[PDB]
Length: 49
Length: 48
Image (tube, rainbow over all chains, first blue to last red):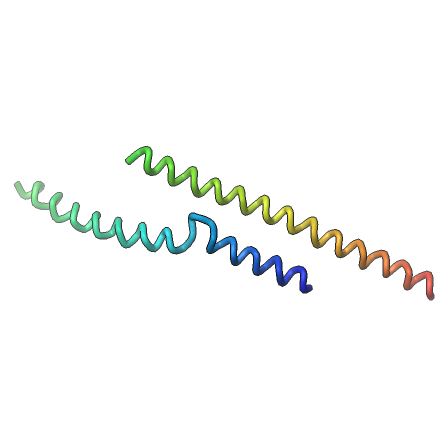
């Protein structure tokens, strides 16, 4: 059981040390969302043109 | 942008593979512990 406990924790460590962690997606989302909204305003303006 | 999304997929896969490797390694550790348990289980029956 202690062995399983350590294994569970090493997986938690993995989920933070791996590059593709929640921090990556949080960053990518925030950044892309800013781009997407800005792109949108421009796309609309041209549709209107 | 295509190199970008391509790299992103590579990274996600690189990590997914590292995870499967981790999980199989762990499985071996538990099996070994379980073998020690089965050995004691037999000794118990021999004691009976």
